[PDB]
Image 1 (cartoon, rainbow, N blue to C red):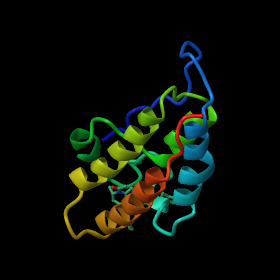
Image 2: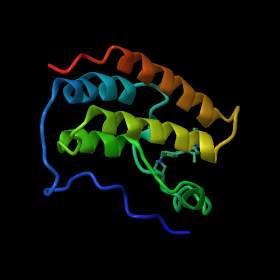
Image 3: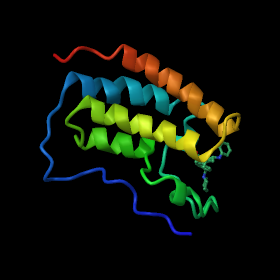
Length: 127
Ligand SMILES: CC(=O)N1c2ccc(-c3ccc(CN4CCCCC4)cc3)cc2[C@H](Nc2ccccc2)C[C@@H]1C
């Protein structure tokens, strides 16, 4: 019926650092995923009102999208690269949870997930 507030993208109390891994996650991984033809359902939080999906935020309790991930990286929100990778993982599993095997949106998520996994397999060593 009503959308929750979007996930936090900035907290001035959180300690910050810039690493080559987080740089890679923003400059390569997110950049590549963003421009993929199937990215568009994932570029912003699910607006369950506009989409008229009253059960979405009843089923999905940890929302995540790429707009939020991107603002996180841009804000130096992430200390660990694994925080960011987990957020991409939550976004994908959210899609598979709410929707059903064989739905168009699930086929789109799957293709995005394989691209993501390929790019994280080439994640540089901390340096
Ligand atoms: C990410 C996800 O699981 N979903 C999602 C999340 C977001 C969106 C979505 C995102 C952006 C728009 C575009 N804007 C809509 C509001 C007005 C301005 C344009 C529309 C739907 C769709 C969808 C999915 N539907 C869909 C429809 C056609 C093709 C592919 C998927 C269901 C599902 C709840």
